[PDB]
Length: 139
Length: 139
Image (cartoon, rainbow over all chains, first blue to last red; front, side):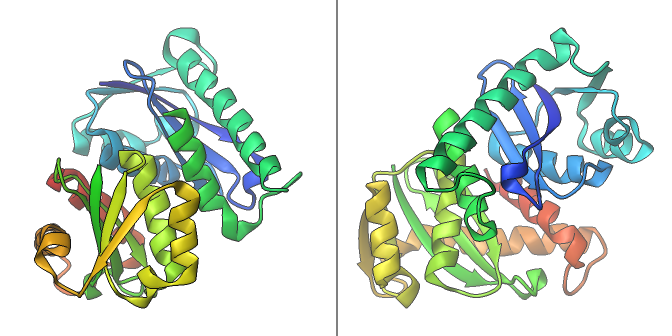
């Protein structure tokens, strides 16, 4: 398994509107979690969840954002025995599949939310299940 | 897919020490989430997560706890098209596999926690990743 991971901003999910998104490259399966801020520890929390969902990957591709190049994240990945490659934001080889997942997720979130009567932000108490439904639907 | 679901109390995970545990009967895969209280909505939040991890099941077996027999939970399951069977707490046919999962999970949580130097409660900031690690290890 080789994953692509990024963060994408989704105000429908505010306050925890920073979505950490992983796509498994061979299967196209997605894992998404919500966060208040993009940080090294948010990335690590996200991947911990993703490992529990998909298994432990051999490698993860990210961009060169601080949250991915930090000593903390380097060490977390090493502790897990997961290889890491980084490129510039949006590079195709390492980020095009996760960027597609971002777009698919945002469209799905919008459609579900609007279907439930939410034309703008999703009420806080409804976000977790809606996000899980979007993940289910896409996978 | 037929699941067995229950709640089990794990003080190492306090304050959100109520663990909602699902086992997929054919694969023995487990999904676990943390909760502060056993409620109908906690069960629903748990299953929403479980569907995102395992897929939508045909049926779920639980005990006859309030959180499972409520109008709210009946309706949530119906909305999802998931059949439900209930029995007395601990009944074998519908709860023995999830009770085994409870025991496997609690042992794993203890071993991981003690390995990290936590002889009693796990620090709050460390619980989510430790729980995800336990789920990964068991699956």
